[PDB]
Image 1 (cartoon, one colour):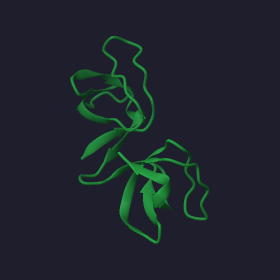
Image 2 (spheres, one colour):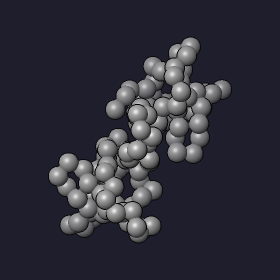
Image 3 (tube, helix red, strand yellow):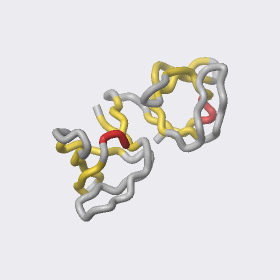
Image 4 (cartoon, helix red, strand yellow):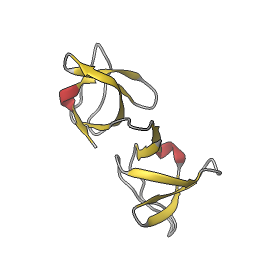
Length: 111
């Protein structure tokens, strides 16, 4: 299992982790529920856990590339979503952290 940033976090303190949507984060210390400690590349630091999403082993992470309302899920440009199942008919099920459902393969780019 691994973690991806859902949102931008800008470091406010020296020991803050700074990161962008889509970056992979290795969690060191998840003992505190307001502030986890983790690492990106060489940098170690603190960040708020709500800013990242856990991803199953071998799951695929995508950035939404175009705002699209569905009939079967809505998503906005630059959202981070996790892919569920395999594609079919130009769509695949993607998970937002709160909603699950089918979204156009062509409005996604993998990260």
